[PDB]
Length: 29
Image (cartoon, rainbow, N blue to C red):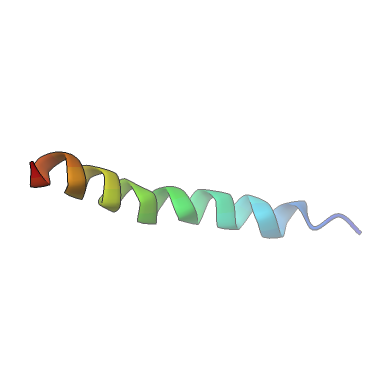
């Protein structure tokens, strides 16, 4: 009924991908 698990998984996965971008940019400098 509630697609909470779907979004919940994506939300967590996004953090992993976003973590690299953030750490990559920060250090890039």
